[PDB]
Amino acid sequence: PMMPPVGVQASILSHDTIRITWADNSLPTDSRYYTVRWKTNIPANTKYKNANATTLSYLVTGLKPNTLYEFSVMVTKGRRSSTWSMTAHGATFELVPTSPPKDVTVVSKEGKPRTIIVNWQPPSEANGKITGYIIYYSTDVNAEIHDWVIEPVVGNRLTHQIQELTLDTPYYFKIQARNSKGMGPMSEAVQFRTP
Ligand SMILES: *[C@@H]1O[C@H](CO)[C@@H](O)[C@H](O)[C@H]1NC(C)=O
Image (cartoon, rainbow, N blue to C red; front, side, top):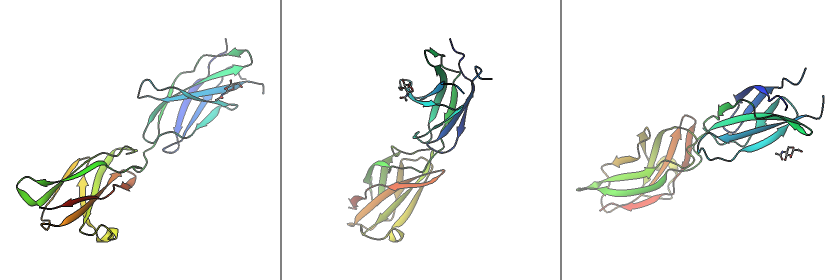
């Protein structure tokens, strides 16, 4: 039985890249190769992805942003092979949201016709901790973004009330998520006509 690699470390490079490094004790030049394996910590049922390396490091790419991964290495030299090394852990950096806030809806507030309530769900691809949202509304759907009225939502709140709206007026609403990295994409405009 071959000696498994030691001193396994993870170096975070981006939202999709982690460098894995290790040491091989069976070295003081031959046909040996290392196999790096990784899977996300959660869900616990995740199948391992793996790659071969001929050096004492491997660049794990195509990872998901803001995700914790487990890494382990083994060595093979022909018919002989080792077990999996100690596990190294590494969580990719955050990235701007890459998806809009889901399930956007607008209702009129109970007994307040000039008041509306916006309701939504966090984006599917938040890619980090949501630091807020930005609501935009307009009487004209085709108006340039600066012409839309800005209504910021602080923190991961999933509701926001907008008061003093013109009656019997069709309004248009769209939202974008915000994280430590910036603004994500906008939702498709939802139309709502005030009573
Ligand atoms: C690594 O090399 C071995 C031997 O050539 C092979 O069985 C294995 O499929 C290779 N790894 C990948 C990721 O295909």
